[PDB]
Image (cartoon, rainbow, N blue to C red; front, side, top):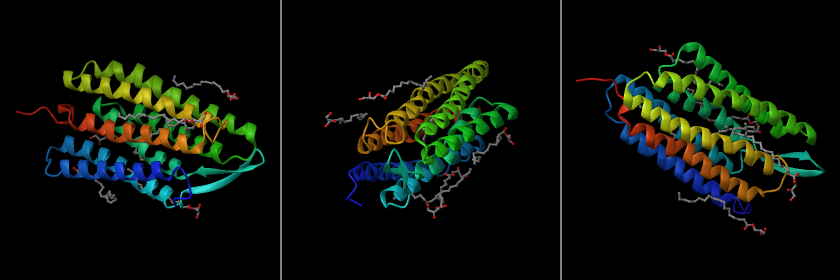
Length: 231
Ligand SMILES: CCCCCCCC/C=C/CCCCCCCC(=O)OC[C@H](O)CO
Ligand SMILES: CCCCCCCC/C=C\CCCCCCCC(=O)OC[C@H](O)CO
Ligand SMILES: CCCCCCCC/C=C\CCCCCCCC(=O)OC[C@H](O)CO
Ligand SMILES: CCCCCCCC/C=C\CCCCCCCC(=O)OC[C@H](O)CO
Ligand SMILES: CCCCCCCC/C=C\CCCCCCCC(=O)OC[C@H](O)CO
Ligand SMILES: *C/C=C(C)/C=C/C=C(C)/C=C/C1=C(C)CCCC1(C)C
């Protein structure tokens, strides 16, 4: 375990996702409003899944070796198992906040599945040049998601309760900045061109993951937007 220099960031990531899960679980105890219950359930599940997949990486289960470029390269495949389930949940929190129509939700979740699934194929591909073909397809799926969040969701939020509009705008901006960083880290890190070493890459994804999951949830669950309007 300690024989891998990145273990300290995996240990810190496990601890922070675990503590985040417990805080949201205790906070949501006794919430009775049905609309608020939905946001607490979605938002508490996100760090609980990431906790399990950080632990699997720390203990060494979620790592495999992929030959390319005449080397055996360590690839943490557990990240994609986490993101397959947690990235659609985070998009569902945003879509429920703006009362998105069912067709737009399906479009978003399906494009997200394509983004993560092609990321995994690129991560496990043994022909070096083809890894970047899958990266480009996955990045095109991400750009579709960001387009909808700006030119679909913003338009509808603006016609809703003012607290819904202001909380959506903030969460939208957090999401666009943080999600856009992931394809860059992958391209310069050990899965791509190999310029940044694996221990620094693991630090960068841990800062991004905690911010995009526990930071995002702290903003959302402190807002009055998740409660129905009631006397
Ligand atoms: C909100 C409060 C928390 C704030 C925390 C945010 C920091 C995020 C981490 C960033 C990158 C820093 C990576 C550390 C730099 C190591 C690079 C290096 O030193 O490599 C040298 C090499 O030996 C010769 O080139
Ligand atoms: C050190 C601590 C480690 C971290 C803990 C280990 C995580 C794995 C265990 C359990 C799943 C617990 C339940 C996860 C689902 C929570 C959903 C929820 O909060 O629902 C609220 C809603 O209001 C209800 O109707
Ligand atoms: C609303 C939807 C909520 C969805 C909640 C789902 C949470 C699932 C969490 C965790 C375990 C993931 C386990 C992944 C198992 C992969 C095992 C495997 O195939 O390993 C192959 C081989 O043995 C070695 O490489
Ligand atoms: C493996 C990747 C896929 C599984 C990962 C799990 C992610 C979340 C699940 C589903 C999105 C499907 C559409 C769900 C949108 C329904 C929300 C809605 O429109 O409202 C309906 C409600 O009945 C009004 O009262
Ligand atoms: C809209 C927000 C999301 C946008 C996300 C898409 C961004 C794509 C950016 C850049 C490609 C730059 C490629 C630079 C890679 C060259 C690396 C190389 O081979 O150089 C060797 C190294 O520099 C010797 O030390
Ligand atoms: C909880 C973790 C989050 C919000 C992770 C988000 C991950 C992405 C937006 C990843 C995107 C990628 C690409 C667009 C292309 C290359 C590979 C990926 C999967 C890193």
